[PDB]
Every structure is written in C-alpha cells, then in structure tokens.
Image (cartoon, rainbow, N blue to C red; front, side, top):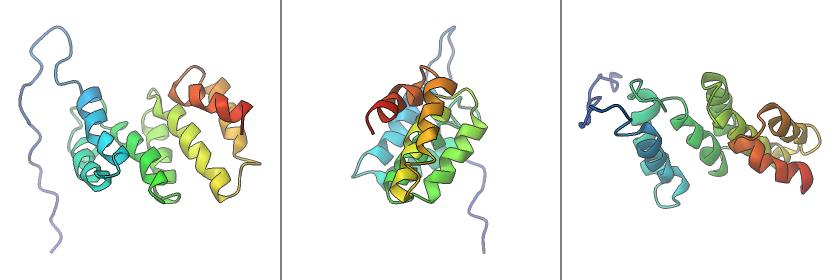
Length: 146
C-alpha cells in the first residue's frame, strides 16, 4: 500500500565505545555518498545515503549526508532536485561545510540555468559569508575565474 518506511537497520554494529569517534559518520557517509560521486554508484548512493539522511539520526552527518547528495544529485542533471537538496542541507546543517560547499556547487548550477549574473553573487557570498569553508574555498575560484 505505502508502508515502505518501517524503522529498522539503525544499528549496523560497532557502536563507538571509546573517548574518540569510532564508525565516524564522516567517513562512512563520505563513503556512502562517495557513491553518488561514483559514476557507477549514483544509485548506490541514493540507497547508501538514504540510510544516512533518513535512517541515521544517530549519525552526526544525517544532514550532510544529504549534502553530498545536494551537490552530486544536481550534477546528475537534477539541477532542480539537488538544487533544493542543498537548500535543505544548507538549512538543516548550519555548521556543515555543505552550507558553503553546495552554496558553491549548487551555487554553480545557477549559471547552468542562467544566473551567472545573479547567483554568481552566491559564490561571492560563500567566500566571505562561508569563509574558509569547503564552499568558500572552491567558490573563490568562481569569484576569480568564472
């Protein structure tokens, strides 16, 4: 009918039992969504990360796992869909690098759609607004180059 969202598969294993982080969401998610980046795993990410952004509230990168999706899903030709993905993560994660990163990268699609005039300003923003962050770092090139 439409009940394809039963809460399960939350405990994968390990369960950090140290003073440091173990099973870093950073790494496992960067590994999940690295799939989106992977031109052979664009779908395997959507399945990977679905585990992250929806089924891993417990994981730090719950929001940002969507980040990697916000950039890459866009570059998948979802110049619409991930464009809002970013909007979601930049929103959700105020402290993520994604707020910058996809500010930069989804900050990129604009020109693709035709806001290299307006949205180019987006870049200028990350550089100064998101300064020295994943986005501001790469957006600096767009501020200077393109």
